[PDB]
Length: 588
Ligand SMILES: Nc1ncnc2c1ncn2[C@@H]1O[C@H](COP(=O)(O)OP(=O)(O)NP(=O)(O)O)[C@@H](O)[C@H]1O
Ligand SMILES: [Mg+2]
Ligand SMILES: [Zn+2]
Ligand SMILES: [Zn+2]
Ligand SMILES: [Zn+2]
Image 1 (cartoon, rainbow, N blue to C red):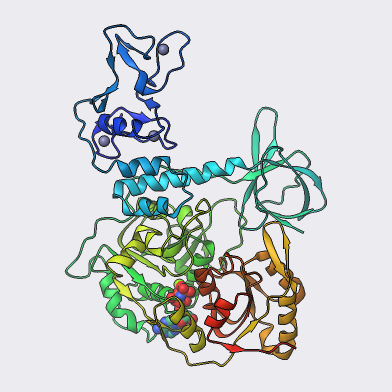
Image 2 (image 1 turned 120 degrees about the vertical axis):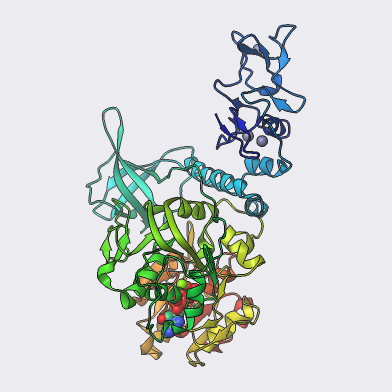
């Protein structure tokens, strides 16, 4: 027994065909079952024909007789429909209102999440539906991981190398660092977890959360996480204040964070505040300075990726007392991340943690950085677990989004990423930093006229070290990713002529190209995903292919805006090459 998801009308009915089983009132249950393929209803007992040897679970055929339910063919003459005239028989069959926006609920519950419009509706609906939509999406995504087959240990070559065998009749997941597996040891009458594992193609290379000596017969499946019911909203009700509440501002502040003191005051004058900033404009710098303006306040810094949280940790290292910081890493995951703070010291003034690894705790201010990669599920988790006085949502909708791996056909705008990005595109951000304080003028001019509507201002001047070369090269593939060796050879010859560029960071859309360029060039390699929130003096980027993946403007924007001094872009698509306001080089 619970509350309807479309009315809040008390009811005992749930839809069994919905993969989330939401409470539905008598009218809503009727409105849903008559217009969709969903016909199973769950009350105290599932509505099913009490006739011996009958299968009818469809509520549209069932009738009530005494204390049992019968189908259309096994019903007595005096028997009444369970679902008729617009309602469904159930507890509280009389406190049933009826929603006007049930058309939305039907589309959300029945869509496969392969079109952008399915995600548009999941962000433009009511708040009660946003939580439901995020549950259905995450459950759909987690259910789609079961379509891949099991991988078992066939042969152990060494430690960091394996031979795998694949469960028949099912496809194989892509082998790279993005996809994390779980290993199991087969016991007598059960199965026990061995840790976390990731695989790459050399015979496969492996790294584990443990040093376990995996033997033949152990198996790996994509790590699936529990979909939790969402209670707290994506955004709490907005409260505006008349003075600063709960916080005591500092008397003297450093000259770096002096330009944000007006915005820092606005943070403490309202329940939640949004800061939109183009790349390299000081959004994360804004977040760490907030701690210095409210020295007594306890701030929780969170983001959706371990990379973005590490970026905040690096800045916090420079500006905050190191003995007041902590990095929250989840139990028994090796995944290498910033360990210059105390690890898993939840009761510190400053806490740096990932969204899905958040502990249930209070804070004075909550800072959510890189908001473009967030989802409504993430926003709900943050309000659920972190109870704070102030919520600061920081990010750039024109940077990396959350991976919507089931989204296939169509283009989703940044305005439909999540409810916080929805505010930034409609009513505007509460705060805004419009001056890029990191990249040279050539990069800023490129991204300003490319994606930021010529509204991005540069603080740095032309460094004259931003170069672009047009070489398609030779594209070679292994399964998921791709490799362009001639484009790497261009960098190799370039690296001799510019010896100040072998400390540079190599960026590429494909991480097989990263591995190949790491072996031949021997440079530090970062993916666009792994470079988020980070800045490097010199960046070398090879586009590798002209595929739709490599030509993504947001992905391309993030990659080239990582450089603070110089960048070299080996482009394959002339459309993006000509839109680069760099200096062109000549072929040898
Ligand atoms: N007021 C400031 N004083 C000194 N350095 C600053 C200031 N604002 C920004 N910077 C520097 O400019 C760079 C950009 O800041 P940062 O906060 O990392 O960018 P960002 O807003 O997070 N862009 P992104 O990587 O998309 O998150 C960093 O090197 C900062 O140290
Ligand atoms: Mg940032
Ligand atoms: Zn349903
Ligand atoms: Zn209802
Ligand atoms: Zn029957």
